[PDB]
Image: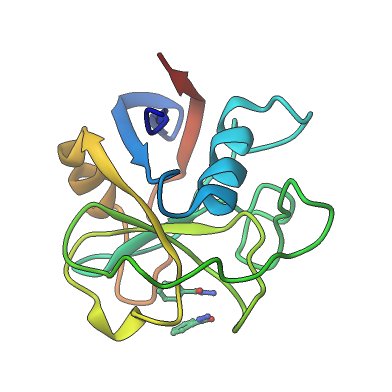
Amino acid sequence: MVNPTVFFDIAVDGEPLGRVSFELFADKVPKTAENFRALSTGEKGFGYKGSCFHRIIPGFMCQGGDFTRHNGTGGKSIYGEKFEDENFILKHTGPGILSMANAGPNTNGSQFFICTAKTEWLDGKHVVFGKVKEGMNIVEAMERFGSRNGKTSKKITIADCGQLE
Ligand SMILES: NNC(=O)c1ccccc1
Ligand SMILES: NNC(=O)c1ccccc1
């Protein structure tokens, strides 16, 4: 069956920036794809709507998904506990790759990152589960609000999000 597509509507200090959409590789990493899909639709009662990208490092990645502590210390999966690395079949091949942030082996929650370059040193440590489909230019625009230590100069939020048909 067809890989799900998800959208994020991004804002910058509350002003709309644009829409980023993602293909989720449910064919390769179903548990991981399903956690991100469900957190994007908010169908379990919690998820990414209203959350922020808290750590953005230009030339590297944009990291988000901490909807409980807003700083990289929090977040939770849909499974009632952190979950295992599903596989490492897919690699960090370039800009647009969507991959799980974690605290080491088998500690996936809800935090994720969008690569803005090839980051092959993350292969085998972070589960790749999707890719930007449309709106890579919005991620490039977001990136410009990061910094060398990752602190953002403006608040970058997921004003809206959901699943696309
Ligand atoms: N907790 N941070 C992470 O899992 C991470 C993810 C991607 C790049 C660098 C760090
Ligand atoms: N899981 N990876 C991390 O927490 C990390 C954070 C900062 C730099 C490199 C790696």
